[PDB]
Image 1 (tube, one colour):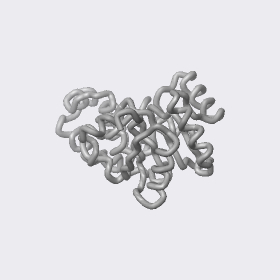
Image 2 (tube, rainbow, N blue to C red; image 1 turned 30 degrees about the vertical axis):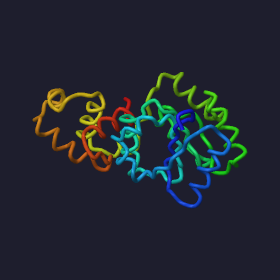
Image 3 (cartoon, rainbow, N blue to C red; image 1 turned 60 degrees about the vertical axis):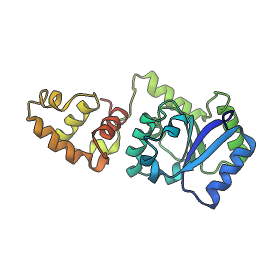
Length: 217
């Protein structure tokens, strides 16, 4: 419906998902549709994906091999959509959440629907639904200067690989990189082909975007 918020839940489709989907559409003003993480890449260049204004992320079905596909789907189609995490574990390392650039709310694994409906209603009112701890972590981290949290796949790359990837996440060219490290253009190109694993980039664009989101010096 044109009136309602375009929401997209990133999850499995199944008895429960659909059951929550309907529950969310009963109480809040939204048109929700469910898309599994595994299929994100198929929605990247769809027109109707450009209309997504909220993404609801089932933290329980998230995994490292989807992260890359997500970051690009998010940039290519709905960079400006709000993101809301649900089913988040209690003992989560909040910095791990900075990776969601429009995080607007977080719901924990053992919150109930009373909380979820309350929370989501606030977020639909352009509030944010965070705990005091999390709000503090953001503030301490941001206030202290830091913008991005360098991720874990990164630290696992070789020295070449690391240097080559940082510069990529600076939108440098093949040539421009080969010229700051003093190496064959064809060389950086070969390192990159490796680096796409495990960072899991289907291509240079994914990696580039992966980069700008997952590595800050």
